Amino acid sequence: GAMNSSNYAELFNNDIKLFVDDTNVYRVTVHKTFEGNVATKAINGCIFTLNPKTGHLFLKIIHTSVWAGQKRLSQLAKWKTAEEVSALVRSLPKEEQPKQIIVTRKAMLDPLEVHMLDFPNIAIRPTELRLPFSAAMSIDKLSDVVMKATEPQMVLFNIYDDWLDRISSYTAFSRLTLLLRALKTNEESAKMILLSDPTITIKSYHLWPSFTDEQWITIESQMRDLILTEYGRKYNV
Amino acid sequence: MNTVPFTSAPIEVTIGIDQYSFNVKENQPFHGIKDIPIGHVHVIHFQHADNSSMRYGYWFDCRMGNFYIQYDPKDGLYKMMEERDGAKFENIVHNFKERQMMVSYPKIDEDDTWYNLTEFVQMDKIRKIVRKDENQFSYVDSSMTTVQENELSDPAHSLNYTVINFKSREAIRPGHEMEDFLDKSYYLNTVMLQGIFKNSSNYFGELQFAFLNAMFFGNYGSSLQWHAMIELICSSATVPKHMLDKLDEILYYQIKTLPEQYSDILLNERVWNICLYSSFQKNSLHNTEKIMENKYPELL
Ligand SMILES: Cc1ccc(OC[C@H](O)CN)c(C)c1
Image (cartoon, rainbow over all chains, first blue to last red; front, side):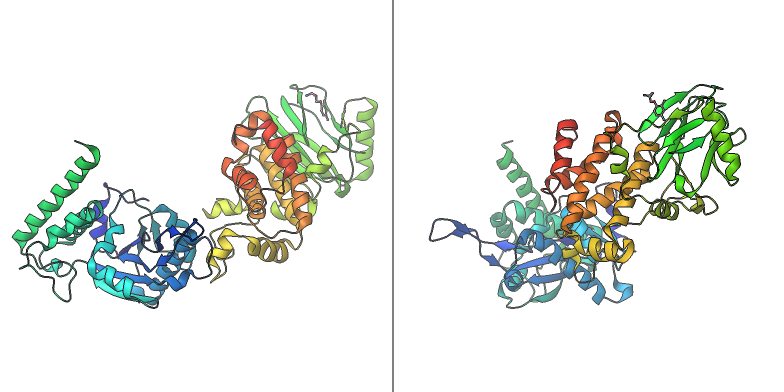
């Protein structure tokens, strides 16, 4: 069924699974026409496909050329996402194919189900959780590679960096979702927190700074404070 | 004008014949229905007074045999049987009419309701959906499940309707995923009409038969099947123009005939609101849309 708080540890068991987020597939800049109407111009997007156990990220970059001459782009975006996910599964060796795919928005269920008819033993699941994956484009290196792309392109990342050398997947996912929830609620401040100390750097082969265990505690605390605050500033509490 | 005689009526029962019903008392002197119109299939059906559980009945065509009803006190139901001896049958029927022990099929002149509900229903096709080849008539009841149902348990007592599944490979061409899911014309016109049913009349006949089994027996799998076949047409952008106009007529009479007090269970809100207000064919069902609004504006 649906993934929720009750069955949250299934994510870190040994059955391969992927989250699919489509929030950033179709992106625009609504603007004004010389005639005073409004027109959109698309920019490059991405599918966020993530193995929550291993941190492997399959970042499919959606180039603006995909949309040319197409109608009803918000609906196409969902079928284009489902086509790309099924192509990814097909490209993987059988022993690497997921046993479940969890979509972060329920409107992806039918598109993905239809594109995956050839894989009847892969379960397509919604979730009740409000995961903050839309904020993946606030990670500078991911945003950079999407915006520089001149053609369709798949880029592979580990979104946990080397954290799994020291912490479990469960803890790694919790750090990721906290970091992403903070960037989604107040990107400016979240980035100020992560980069304030010029002595903490991001390795060329990583996405996040090189924090000690103690420094990660301090960072996580600061991210929590920001999320509650903005919850205050947003709700006046 | 043909006749279905009854040996007797030992238990109290509501008897139905097409869209009509009447009550017979326990051991009332009752020996059948005469003046049944030739040229149509018919259905004669039963609901016991003592146990409204199980509506059941028999589809038949009087041109294919002499049929009569006889209660079975072992199996506990009114059974249809064929009489092979022609002069035995005429003589039995003739005696029962002389004694005026038979009720008359009240075919009011002006009325074409039955014709319009069974226009495309053939006995030959009924008997492929309901497999029991030693008989010329077909038994159906409330509880019989469909082939598609048994996939999701006795195959002999099943309803072999054509399986329709909008999220299946039969329905969805590789590389046309989105196209074929949002516009089902491929599945309707190529897979089903050209491939399986061969023509629209056979398609309409199964649609009509599914609805009648849903209405008369409360057969849930038949209602599923009726709705599926409507949705496949309403969700195809390309349908032959003659099929669209006929469909409006077909549905109109089904909605007209439905008991008002049964609409809560026999009509699927989603299918009808999609067909009437959102689908490709939302503008091609004027008569059906009019009667659904005068009569069931609540569901909508
Ligand atoms: C063959 C047949 C059809 C209808 C009949 O009367 C229906 C009447 O309204 C009582 N409900 C009878 C008695 C026979």
